[PDB]
Image (cartoon, rainbow, N blue to C red):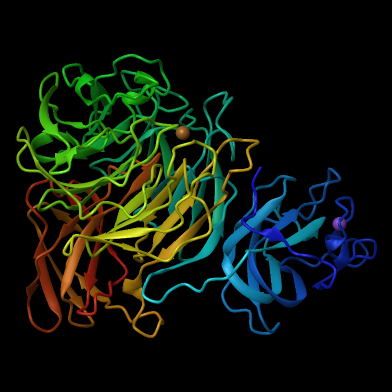
Length: 639
Ligand SMILES: [Cu+2]
Ligand code: NA
């Protein structure tokens, strides 16, 4: 099930309009309170007008609207199920503006919702762009509008949330398709559940930021239910999905051909392991006792060229285990892995003990000391997040999480780890005064400017329960060593939520739930627009443009020359992300040093160490003196 974020608005005073309505199926059947009666557009002998179809409500007064619900026809017939849709709000009835929510609803008879940030309005309009099966009708048994207890205007200068993208599934795992710019999301064998999978199938969905189209596709070619997996973008730019519901499988997503390819089976069955791309394009994984059995799962490495998984038995998982009260089932999960120099992998946590993993020969592991600072040794931080915001300086920001996977209080701990050469003990300090809000199950992304956006989570980890939610996101500004609260959102994003940086510089945050009959499934995502995209007036700022790129494919050590339309002050390269269960081992940022060639022409070199400039796809962003970033240019970094 799902749920709206507000309380139902009284339908007494409403006035509704429909594009068409067949007698027996009047506009008002949708607001009678009877689930047996429904509005239905013209059919048969009234003709069959194709969608779009529209449902407009006049609440007569101004309500602080935060959502709507749509109960499809409950008579067993599917005709008229809304697929693609848009939701608009208006205080006047003539000026709608941009949709407050849009996307596609799954093809079933369950009540569907549109949850969105609170906006005073008197008029609401639901546009049915498509019928779920491609037919021309639109039918609605019941329609409700929800209101917030109050309305609090976003504060200027603190970012903005919206719109809401409605999806057919709970996006508990997502990736950006680098060649297309689309967001790829997946659930499990079902749109809203993973328990009871016959294994072998995964439901996916994609959102295209350019067209606003949400599409769904079932993947069975790899015979893998991809819930709870390791995810890494390999050296070739293929996304490597491992284990989870089908514990030994490997599935490859090729952005180029937009297809799924069966990969080789891992040597050890795992679920909830983290995998990390290496300086050589290979993928290392360790741990993962969620599925495949509970025992010590040492390292293994995938080679994209030979398409083999090789065991690395001496890359021992033992030193990275947390002290989880549930034991090994949780203690080897979601490692904070980072590919580094010379085939090494750094594990920053969640255990207090940090380690160096080596992939030569049969593997090795060396202690890197304890995450700690002048405030003491950091406790285990299961589901805390770790982000490499400056790969050149080896800087990793870690934050949040709790000692145990669940039933444990999250903390405000935050540290900065600075990596040197593999085998050396990195320096760790405390970050500022820690998070404003203790959280676990939160997600984060590094932004073009090197700041880290942190959002969602809860104060006490309770999977599938939307309790103690943190609605206020925070940004860490490394240059100032300061955290800043941002404007709050209205949708809880806790266990099974995700965040990804979009190529336009905005953040896509969504998911949460995936517990079948629970009412905590969130079949949506919201967009957060950081203040760097607005000018002083609250309007969107004018962005620099990258008019030319000497090349779109470069070897580490290589130079790229660009021309822009305005003088730029800074540039950064951001590796494309993948995310699930708080883990994102693919994102990282490299700040660039620019050579001004005069005439708004600039060159830069990609770092020559492929353990810094990990191979794969990256986003190039340039910023003007104002700090406004361009939309990214996609660059492929090869070794
Ligand atoms: Cu899970
Ligand atoms: Na009705």
